[PDB]
Amino acid sequence: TDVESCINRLREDDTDLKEVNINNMKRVSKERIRSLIEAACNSKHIEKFSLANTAISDSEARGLIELIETSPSLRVLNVESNFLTPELLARLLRSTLVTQSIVEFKADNQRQSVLGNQVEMDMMMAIEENESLLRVGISFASMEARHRVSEALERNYERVRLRRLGK
């Protein structure tokens, strides 16, 4: 992937750039990754943004909050296998409620795997309120969270199925 080109295109709100995938690109300077995320905020067309295994941490991923809360088109966000903290992940998921454009949010296998009770309770309630999410790549230890999340995702899947059928 051409990170530099993506940055320029996203900033100009390129109507054709729908997918940006920089998975496994650990070489990219963190300032560039930060600029890429910031650029994505200007696009009302981007549908998929993947930064899996790019060795990013909270400092580089914080900008995703603005992207998620601003984007009306982002459908898939993948930040798995990085160094993001449970607290930041909770904030990212809660931010999905602003526009609810995202249907797939994957963030499993972070270096710090244990989310902790407070984070799981945050996430389960945020997800339960989200009507668009169909897939959430997060491992919960809490029975209640697992159950409420599964139910919410299934509820959302049924909402889509019925809409496809004309209700």
Image: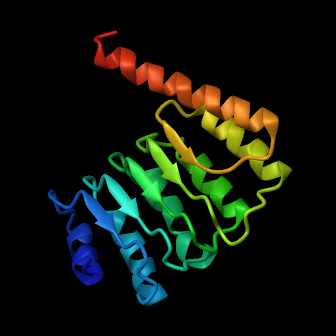
Q: Extreme left residue here?
A: 16
- In the displayed structure, 162 sits above or below 152; it is above
Q: The C terminus lies in which quarter of the figure?
A: top left
Q: Residue at x 52, y 54 (%)?
A: 106
Q: x, y (%) of residue 13?
A: 21, 62
Q: x, y (%) of residue 136?
A: 56, 45
Please state if 150 lies on the left or on the right of 113 as rendered. Answer: left
Q: The N terminus lies in which quarter of the figure?
A: bottom left
Q: Residue at x 44, y 90 (%)?
A: 29
- In the displayed structure, 57 sits above or below 124; it is below
Q: x, y (%) of residue 52?
A: 47, 68
Please state if 135 lies on the left or on the right of 86 as rendered. Answer: left
Between 4 and 55, the one nearer to me in the picture: 55
Q: x, y (%) of residue 86?
A: 72, 61
Q: Quadrant of residue 72?
A: top left
- In the displayed structure, 155 sits above or below 167; it is below
Q: Residue at x 67, y 54 (%)?
A: 90
Between 27 and 129, the one nearer to me in the picture: 27
Q: Quadrant of residue 46?
A: bottom left
Between 94 and 77, the one nearer to me in the picture: 77
Q: Residue at x 43, y 45 (%)?
A: 102
